[PDB]
Amino acid sequence: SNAPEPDMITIFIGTWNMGNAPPPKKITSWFLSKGQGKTRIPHDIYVIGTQEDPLGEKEWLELLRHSLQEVTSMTFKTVAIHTLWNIRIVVLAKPEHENRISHICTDNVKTNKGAVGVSFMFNGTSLGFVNSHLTSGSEKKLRRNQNYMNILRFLALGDKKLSPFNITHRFTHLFWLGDLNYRVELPTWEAEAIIQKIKQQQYSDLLAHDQLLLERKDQKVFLHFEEEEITFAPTYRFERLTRDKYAYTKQKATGMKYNLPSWCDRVLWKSYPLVHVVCQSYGSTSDIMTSDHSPVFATFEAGVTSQIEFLACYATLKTKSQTKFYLEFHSSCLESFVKSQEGANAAGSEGELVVRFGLPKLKPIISDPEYLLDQHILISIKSSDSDESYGEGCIALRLHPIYTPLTHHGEMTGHFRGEIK
């Protein structure tokens, strides 16, 4: 008898800045999650992002497929490969999944730096993957933040019918990896102390100065993304062919400069509310030494799948606009997206607008509760004057009151609250 489709899959994410050098003949440690770092069987999907990648596409594919044969005893199939400059993403999957995978998309954004991405459906679940190489230099964190903002706005992945939504709402699970280039922000006179803290494996004191964690805390990038705790050493910048020494100085015509050891190479994720996702490993290798960066691995278990009445809903927006607003509801469980009538505007606290709705009844294509309880509704609040979104969010149907933050262009713009039946 036909077995039920999987309710969970496992996903390997790798990111490696290859430093423009060919890889060594053995890279299996990367796929085995062998190295320092948090931990909680071949994976269903392998996503391999490289930067400063010097190889051709078919050359690198054959090295990966052979390495995975040795690790898993299976021959993985190519789902997608996409390259911009020397920034590349490869997605491989078990052969048994080939008929489960549909709507494969690829795209890139130039910001040489930039991003590549791949998205596809696994049965009923959308998955997105972004590999970005962001602006380099300890002093350029604001430019990295802007690179992130431009990638999220302009990378075209996922269902194009989801017109008001960027990649941060288009997927049940979105994974963002790469050489994000954020540095440990400490004075250069502290270099030798940092090296000592690394040898003592005292990472929490250095992570207090990691620009990516600090910019996330201030809501400047990666809003509502998670990252596993980091318990591996900084992955940059090593002398090549060893891992025993960091190369933290750099000669320049204008005098010696510094690249203090940093966690440049990262994996983050954002999943729809109430969907299962758990990180099983996050770490770096120590035996792959052809680059001045070490490869990073992160593995995950992720949940997948095979009338709706919105009641007493209001939005709060930080805006001075006096337009009226309406709502748009989008979901794979609807035959097409649904627009509401205009709400009623009132002032809230300073600079804020409350938009109250006293809303169309949504009719899902399938009414089976085993189907519906796993669905989500994407919500956009749009200006009637311009038809542009002022805020996007997501509600789980897994049953009540409902709530989502609203963002636009990846930054907070307000909140949406109500009840659902």
Image (cartoon, helix red, strand yellow):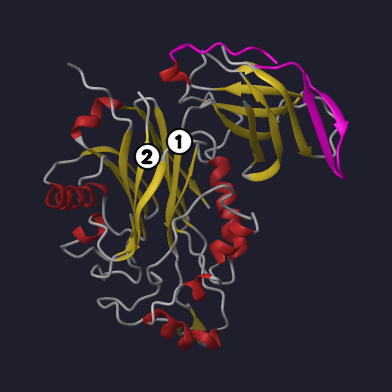
Alpha-carbon span between mark 2 and mark 1: 8 Å
Residue 416 seen from this side: yes
Residue labelled with disc 2: 302
Q: Nearer the viewer, residue 375 or 163?
A: 375
- Residue 225's x, y, as percent? 53, 49
- Provide the residue span drawn in magenta: 339-368
- Residue 97's x, y, as percent? 24, 31
Residue labelled with disc 1: 275
Q: Is residue 216 above or below residue 24?
A: above
* Secondary-structure class at tag 1: loop
Q: Check the picture and name the quadrant holding the C terminus.
A: top right
- Residue 17's x, y, as percent? 36, 62
Q: Earlier in the sequence, mark 2 or mark 1?
A: 1
Q: Residues within 10 Å of mark 2 (few under 14, many from 20)?
A: some
Q: Nearer the viewer, residue 40 or 288?
A: 40
Q: Are marks 2 and 1 in contact (CB under 8 Å)?
A: yes
- At horizontal 86% and vertical 38% (from top left) the residue drawn is 348
Three-letter code for the amino acid on which mark 1 is drawn: Val
- Asked which quadrant contains residue 217, the reply is bottom right
Q: Check the picture and name the quadrant holding the N terminus.
A: top left
Task: From the viewer's perspective, tell me whether residue 217 is left or right of residue 371.
Answer: right
**Residue at the extreme front:** 400
Task: From the viewer's perspective, tell me whether residue 126 is left or right of residue 418.
Answer: left
Q: Is residue 226 magenta?
A: no
Residue 49 seen from this side: no
* Secondary-structure class at tag 2: strand
Three-letter code for the amino acid on which mark 2 is drawn: Ala
- At horizontal 23% and vertical 52% (from top left) the residue drawn is 60
- At horizontal 79% and vertical 25% (from top left) the residue drawn is 356
